[PDB]
Image (cartoon, rainbow, N blue to C red):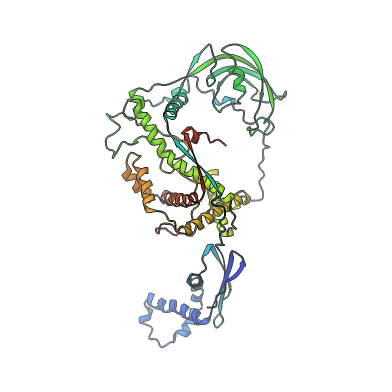
């Protein structure tokens, strides 16, 4: 077979495999002699009729069945000895198939380029040394009690995070709009629920006065013609309602799993659990910043096939979360996925090369290390590990994270890891 | 199909009314939250478990981890198919 290496699309190389009649008529005949044995007709076939008659004439139908066998096995054989590693998927352009003439087929497939790595030492990646200090423990428990607090109607004073009842009436931008009028209205202030500034109109007051404030709607508001407007509302201040914190009695605290009534056990619980989640969160934190700076400091063209693959995974995931559409997503606007997908494969090529050079792997002791730290933190490790190894969707995720961690940390060994000391609040103060 | 046009304007005039995200905590709705009350007593927390490290997942949607067996998400993968040699060819 005459094979080429026609580097047409740069990434796209064309190995035009020209299988001559010597390999055609033998490989077709390999199946034909097996058909006789498979149906046991070979026992009845005396061999009087030479195979050539039943190969070209009677086997003419079967020559079609051998086309895929020729295209598949002779391709994978060729590219290995030609030292050409493919990427994505190969496109077979079958020139012609005839007896006597050559089965010529131009297999156009994309390959990996020379992955340009630069400034990998110049990349400054932040390392937040986050932990659950006593400030974070008390803060955590207090927040839990405030979020699960029972609303107790009081009088006298508005606190910054209370639930205040008013009657407000007016117009937005001096024009009739809905939402600028609500009788017996109630506001859990200090909470991301209403305009910061609307609540502050009330917060500069006590119980049962009457006034009028101008609220400037934020540029954070997705409401296109409201964002940055000034509305005039006559706030009839009625009552206040305290977020009265619930109990922490034996039957309450055990219901969450903390079998001991001692609060120090729930403090210990917050420490061991939130750090179990935290190490994974800090790994993904330093990871995402490293990847951001890696690609921001580096450039590499991706094979279109790989971009198509990532886009397609995003289309399936999109349609699934949009309603549950089966393959309709193939029509979704490619440019919505194009940039981010290609960018994620740029990550895969840059990490691909630093991995290759530093001979990295899905480290068995790392996978298993994280499997023990995972499973032991639950009720029953046994069935979680059994379920895990069989849940290929998640067992994949375990290989992928281990490899991605080691991949990034090989770049961190090269990169300027700017380490800082900070509390568990750090991880939570990530809005935008 | 020809081309069914269903576009009912948009009505982005006064969007995100908000209403302070609150008008439920008024006696009636907290009964629906408290509807059940008694669940999982025991002397301990059901002693048929290997360990009580965290038998009941009290931890919610706090950044990453969460407790439910899934977590994580951001990956890259592929590279050059260097992955642990135990893979089903399933596209």
B60 left or right of A259 in image: right
The foreground one among A40 and A230 is A230
Residue A111 at x, y = what percent? 55, 64
Give above or below for A26 relative to A251. below
Give above or below for A1 relative to B48. below
Give above or below for A163 relative to A305. above
- Residue A126 in sight from this viewpoint: yes
Give above or below for A243 relative to A4. above
State the residue at coordinates (52%, 64%). A86
The foreground one among A280 and A417 is A417
Residue A33 at x, y = what percent? 41, 79
- Residue A319 in sight from this viewpoint: no
The foreground one among A312 and A138 is A138
Q: How many numbered badges does the structure rendering display?
A: 0
Residue A335 at x, y = what percent? 63, 50
The foreground one among A403 and A201 is A403
The quarter of the rendered structure image containing the C terminus of chain A is: top right
């Amino acid at each position: 077979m005459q094979v080429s290496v026609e580097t047409t699309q740069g990434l796209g190389r064309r190995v035009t495999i020209t299988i001559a009649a010597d390999s055609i008529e033998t490989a077709v005949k390999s199946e034909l002699v097996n058909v006789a044995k498979k149906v046991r007709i070979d026992g009845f076939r005396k061999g009087k009729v030479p195979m050539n008659i039943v190969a070209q004439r009677y086997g003419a139908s079967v020559r079609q069945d051998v086309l895929g066998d020729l295209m598949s096995r002779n391709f994978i054989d060729a590219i290995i000895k030609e030292k050409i590693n493919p990427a994505g998927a190969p496109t077979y352009v079958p020139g012609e198939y005839k007896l006597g003439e050559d089965f010529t087929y131009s297999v156009e497939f994309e390959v990996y380029p020379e992955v340009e790595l630069q400034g990998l030492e110049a990349i400054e990646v932040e390392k937040p040394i986050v932990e659950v200090t006593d400030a974070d423990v008390d803060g955590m428990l207090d927040t839990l009690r405030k979020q699960q607090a029972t609303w107790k109607e009081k009088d006298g004073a508005v606190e910054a995070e209370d639930r205040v009842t008013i009657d407000f009436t007016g117009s937005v931008d001096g024009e009739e709009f809905e939402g600028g009028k609500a009788s017996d209205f109630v506001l859990a202030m200090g909470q991301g629920r209403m305009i910061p500034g609307f609540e502050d109109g009330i917060k500069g007051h006590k119980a049962g006065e009457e006034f009028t404030i101008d609220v400037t709607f934020p540029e954070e508001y997705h409401a296109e013609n409201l964002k940055g407007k000034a509305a005039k509302f006559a706030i009839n201040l009625k009552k206040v309602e305290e977020r009265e914190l619930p109990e922490l009695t034996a039957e309450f605290i055990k219901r969450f799993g903390v079998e001991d009534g001692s609060v120090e056990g729930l403090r210990a619980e917050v420490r061991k659990n939130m750090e179990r989640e935290l190490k994974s969160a800090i790994r993904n934190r330093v990871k995402s910043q490293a990847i951001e700076g890696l690609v921001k400091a580096n450039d590499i063209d991706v094979p279109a096939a790989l971009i198509d693959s990532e886009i397609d995974v995003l289309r399936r995931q999109a349609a699934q979360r949009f309603g549950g559409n089966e393959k309709q997503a193939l029509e979704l606007p490619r440019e919505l996925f194009e940039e981010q997908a290609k960018r994620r494969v740029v990550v895969g090529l840059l990490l691909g090369e630093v991995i290759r050079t530093n001979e990295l792997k899905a480290d068995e002791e790392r996978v298993k290390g994280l499997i023990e730290e995972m499973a032991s933190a639950y009720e029953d490790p046994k069935e979680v590990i059994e379920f895990y190894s069989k849940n290929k969707e998640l067992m994949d995720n375990m290989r992928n994270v281990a490899l991605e961690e080691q991949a990034v940390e090989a770049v961190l060994a090269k990169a300027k890891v700017t380490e800082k000391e900070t509390t568990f609040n750090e991880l939570m103060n990530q809005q935008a | 199909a020809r081309a069914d046009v269903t576009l009912g304007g948009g009505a982005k005039t006064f969007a995100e009314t908000a209403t302070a995200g609150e008008w439920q905590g008024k006696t009636l709705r907290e009964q629906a939250q408290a509807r059940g009350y008694q669940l999982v007593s025991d002397a301990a927390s059901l002693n048929s478990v290997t360990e009580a490290n965290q038998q009941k997942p009290l931890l919610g949607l706090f950044a990453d981890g969460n407790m439910p067996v899934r977590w994580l998400g951001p990956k890259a993968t592929y590279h050059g198919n260097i992955d642990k040699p135990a893979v089903t060819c399933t596209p």
